[PDB]
Amino acid sequence: TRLVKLVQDYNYMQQNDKIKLLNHQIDYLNKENTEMDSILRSKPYIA
Amino acid sequence: LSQANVKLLAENSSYLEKLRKTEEILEEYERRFQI
Image (cartoon, rainbow over all chains, first blue to last red; front, top):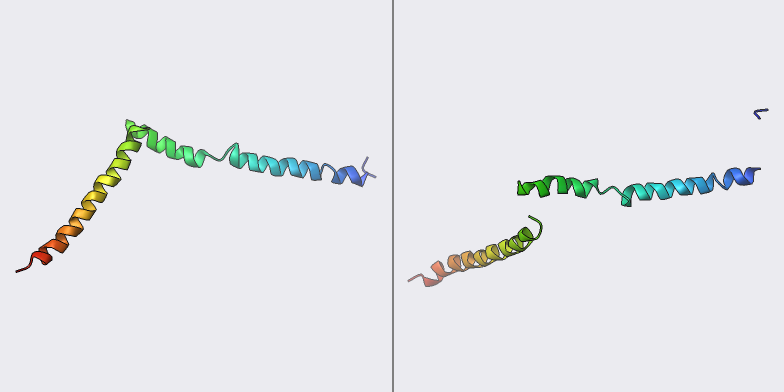
């Protein structure tokens, strides 16, 4: 084991892409804590 | 503080705006009236 490049590149690269997609899901599915922290401030302002 | 504010806030900006205009006009009018 210690002592097919195509798959190492094809996932890694597909794996790499799943991660990049996940990075975007982190931002849109989501990073909305930025806006919802504003909800945490503002909506309680009814109180 | 969901919709009512939104409407009141919109109105607030307007009510203000109206005042902003009258304040400007009054300033202009004192020194329009003059002598």
